[PDB]
Image (spheres, rainbow, N blue to C red):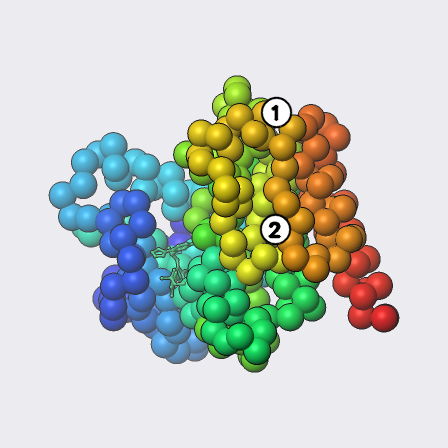
Amino acid sequence: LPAFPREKLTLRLLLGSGAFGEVYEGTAVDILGVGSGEIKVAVKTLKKGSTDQEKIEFLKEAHLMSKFNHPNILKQLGVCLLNEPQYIILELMEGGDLLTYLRKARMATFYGPLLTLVDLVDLCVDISKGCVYLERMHFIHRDLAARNCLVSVKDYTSPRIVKIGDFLPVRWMAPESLMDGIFTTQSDVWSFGILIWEILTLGHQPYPAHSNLDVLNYVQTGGRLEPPRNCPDDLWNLMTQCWAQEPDQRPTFHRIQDQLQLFRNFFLNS
Ligand SMILES: Cc1nc([C@](C)(O)CO)sc1-c1cnc(N)c(O[C@H](C)c2cc(F)ccc2N2NC=CN2)c1
């Protein structure tokens, strides 16, 4: 656990609420080492007056995050858990969540989306690198979706990096998870298929003509999402593999990264 002095942390502004207390955008001095300087951070807080049950759940979240070190996984830079309000200090992803990022790219102008196919393929590749890391660590995510991924830039020109953050969402859940409550790395592969469909559609809601409860049945009955408009067939083929009814027939995250990597190389050669 990376204990950090709260005296070196400034809470600058409110970003949202989340689940335990409030989430702020802040500044942490030398949180990377003694020379580092002032670096922009996001601070997850546990409201003062929280019960022991809430403190234990907050401690569990800090423990979970302390295990990740990957370019495509959100990093916990420090914790301030000795006093109230308790803090979990994270790297600030200035672009915000991927769902909002994708949606704004689509709706900014009728000339076209602010993201191209090669931008969207790079997003898929970057998330799949994160998933390969998680599979290698034996960490089951349970909630892969664009609303849980973050982008490093807010604009659509600068080089960007996407990271997996936030560790029922029926529209993202695998059949076994809906029927038996089974959550494995194979069910995460299902959600990854939904997330790449989110990317290629630029943040459209999965199964738009279905309700949450009709999604529960439609998915158990063999029904899948519609192919995104003009979606390259290699990406649609990969997506349908992710949605195999039986978890054992779905590809591994390492295979998915290879498939995305092959498509990106093939496409760039054209
Ligand atoms: C700067 C910034 N803007 C965001 C918006 C409001 O969603 C706009 O895209 S998230 C965000 C933002 C930037 N960097 C973070 N490290 C962050 O982490 C928080 C804990 C978070 C991580 C997630 F994976 C998903 C949602 C959230 N939020 N969102 C609100 C509270 N927690 C949020």
Q: Residue at x 57, y 49 (%)?
A: 195
- For the C terminus, the quadrant is bottom right
* Mark 2: secondary structure: helix
Relative horizontal placement of residue 122, taking residue 98 as reference (left or right):
right
Q: Position of residue 170 (x, y in %)?
A: 47, 35
Q: Of label 2 and label 1, which has the lower sequence position?
A: 2
Name above or below for residue 221 compared with residue 155. Answer: above
Relative depth, front residue between 262 and 208: 208
Cβ atoms under marks 2 and 1 closer than 8 Å: no
Question: Residue tagged by mark 2?
Answer: 197
Rendered-image quarter of ligand 1: bottom left
Relative horizontal placement of residue 106, taking residue 51 as reference (left or right):
right
Q: Position of residue 68 (x, y in %)?
A: 53, 50
Q: Residue at x 73, y 39 (%)?
A: 241
Give the tally of numbered discs.
Answer: 2
Relative depth, front residue between 218 and 84: 218
Q: Which quarter of the picture shows residue 264?
A: bottom right
